[PDB]
Length: 126
Image: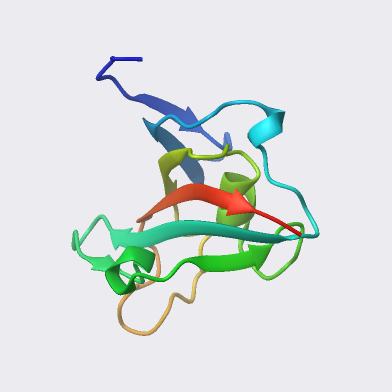
């Protein structure tokens, strides 16, 4: 496990979601998340056009907890989280579709703009 190479993994053929193997975690269903349960993970948002970081869990030093299998998060997080393992830190690129659709958030994310977000599974419970 002393390799220094990354791999690109497209979540959807549409090209709206693409994760990149940054830091391999455990690997296996035993380290997979569970729907309908309080799960705790860490992730940070960053723009590719501006290259700035925003909404970083670490930037404030506070883990975010949520329940999987719910319609509170976009396909980007749902798919990524449902396609990641424990201790698995990777970066997913959300296009201008699965993200905030056509109406981004304020004047920080204008429509028709790709965004990058790094997700990492910390631990889940009930």
